[PDB]
Image (cartoon, rainbow, N blue to C red):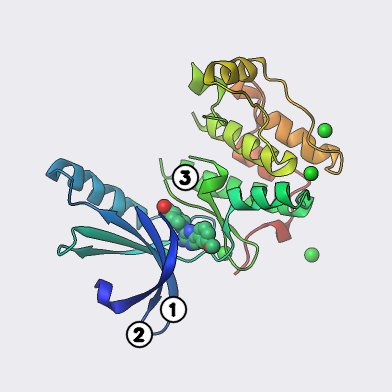
Amino acid sequence: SRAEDYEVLYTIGTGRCQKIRRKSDGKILVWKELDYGSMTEAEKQMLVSEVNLLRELKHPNIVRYYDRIIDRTNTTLYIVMEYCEGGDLASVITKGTKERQYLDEEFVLRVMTQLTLALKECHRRSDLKPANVFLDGKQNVKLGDFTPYYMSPEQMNNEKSDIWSLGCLLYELCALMPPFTAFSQKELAGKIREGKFRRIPYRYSDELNEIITRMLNLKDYHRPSVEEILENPLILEHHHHHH
Ligand SMILES: COc1cccc(-c2cnc(N)c(N3CCC(C(=O)O)CC3)n2)c1
Ligand SMILES: [Cl-]
Ligand SMILES: [Cl-]
Ligand SMILES: [Cl-]
Ligand SMILES: [Cl-]
């Protein structure tokens, strides 16, 4: 549990995220670097609190956080977590736009199934966007992190709010653009409150279109619950995580 136990391979993004290798057994991991040198005792206490709660989230569809490492010489805290070799979903959407190629329905069903189960676990314990959703090396989808395109009408003015955000994310995976677009937040808010959007492309089934649309209902109480989503006939065993 010291930084010297690991070698940095390279920087993933900029605190700063780095792919690292554990020296003892060669295991590939990543860590996030948090410089706490500019923080008050009160801000460091809330940091330690947040980090200890991260450690108890064990679920196949939530990024796994293993360890935390302190380096007082640099006032740097390192959060060691699993490595998701597939990167984030935002980059998958970007790729699709550039290649002018829509994503497979099977892929969208996997994201839906696995993110719905991550949310179910989050709700049971008590920010859904493509940049916070990660892919591993075997088609598994994991929620991480922890212009407001995905802002729900009610949050504009609740576990059903998360359903709205998943609807927006799944819609963007299919259309390669969010359901509501605009140049300012006030214009965005107008579009959102009206609750109209284009059908996802026709290569996607009426059944997939229907459930996404339901998640985007203006009335939180008409959006399907996590349990109602998972009962959908589209969602099969192979859409779930597999080790
Ligand atoms: C090029 O490969 C990439 C691209 C983008 C992200 C990643 C990646 C891989 N594994 C991770 N555990 C990871 N993180 C997911 C969790 C994030 C968080 O808790 O702040 C930090 C970044 N990102 C890899
Ligand atoms: Cl898994
Ligand atoms: Cl296209
Ligand atoms: Cl269309
Ligand atoms: Cl199969």
Residue at point 47% right, 41% down? 123
Give above or below for 135 relative to 209. Answer: below
Dot placed on the residue nearer the N-terminal end, 3 or 1:
1
Position of 122 compared to 212: left or right?
left
Q: Mark 2 and mark 1: span between their CA atoms?
A: 8 Å
The Cα–Cα distance between marks 3 and 1, rounded to whole angstroms, is: 28 Å
For marks 2 and 3, give the CA distance. Answer: 33 Å
Q: Position of residue 87 (x, y in %)?
A: 56, 59
| Residue receiving disc 1 | 27
- Residue 202 picture location, percent across and down: 86, 39
Query: Of the residues shown, which amino acid type is indicated by label 3?
Result: Cys
Side of 117 relative to 95 (left or right): left
Of label 2 and label 3, which has the lower sequence position?
A: 2
- Crowding at dot 3, Cα within 10 Å, few <14 / some 14-19 / many 20+, comes out as some
- Tag on residue 24? 2
The residue carrying mark 2 has its beta carbon less than 8 Å from ligand 1? no
Mark sitting on residue 122: 3
> Is 225 situated above or below 84?
above
Label 3 residue near ligand 1, CB within 8 Å? no
Task: Give the amino acid type for the residue marked by disc 1 in the picture.
Answer: Lys
